[PDB]
Length: 216
Length: 216
Image (cartoon, rainbow over all chains, first blue to last red; front, side):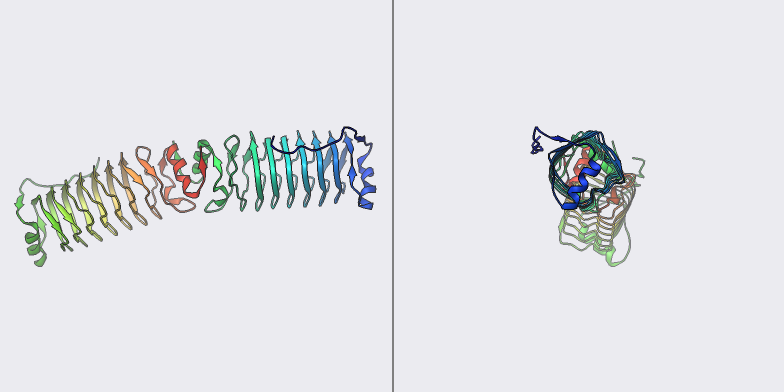
């Protein structure tokens, strides 16, 4: 990786119940710091405006939770299920997602910096108007992810699935798609969003075929 | 070719001086019929509204002449040089071009029927708004030829060089380019003019270059 890793101390306070540990810090507007959460299962809970750093989430399940307006800095999510949780206006810096289920997740208007995700599933998610900078994907399922009006810089991906994506108004100059799956993207006419992008011969033939032309 | 050949009898007179001969038939509004023209060299001459059939041009040179609104039926051009001549609004039926130099000819608004071109050079020529039906190209140089807003039906080509053509609004459904060179075509977005056409994998990677997309 060319990405700065989360900077986490060796001594982490293990925490019992996160749902109510956080209540104090939300109230008083204080950073949650240096903790480890493990084995939780929480649904429909409001964690909006949490300001979290230097912590690890492990084997946790946050379904349909709000993280609207939250921030995460030097944070690992490892083997978590965040499906259908709402992260609109959230901020991420030096974060890692590893082996996570993030189906139907709402990441609209987010800011990501120096973040990597590996072996995780993001099907049916929304990354519209996200601004993402210094990002690395490995083995990521991005099937049916909407990501219109986004702003990407130093974004790389390998072995990842960009299938049925809406890329409308999102410029992809300098992105290399050759070691990934690119299938059935939605783009403008003409297709500026792919100007300066790099694809494979097969990707080009599939794409031309898409627009009604026969290829050998 | 299952294309009707020119139907020319053996009963031909050989004309000495084509310029003089043609003026008589032009002044009297009568058709030129059953002649062989050989070895002429004519420049800047007006043959507009000429009507010519059952005839053969061999080894003739017509530079910057007008055949505007002319008519050619059952005619053969062989080893001719028609470079920069103006055939705008002309009509061609059961004709053949064989080893001709037709650099920069104006074929705008023409009609072609049952016509075949072999070993001929058409570069820098204009074919806009042409109607072409039952056509065969064999070893044709079509470099930098403009052919916008044209109607093509039963069009076939082989070993021909379609390079840097403007195809804007010319539907090429059914046309097979796999046995030809096709480079740098200009088309609409979406690219309707190649809907239903057949191209090679190499040719598809080239076409997509129009929009600035890079391919390995």
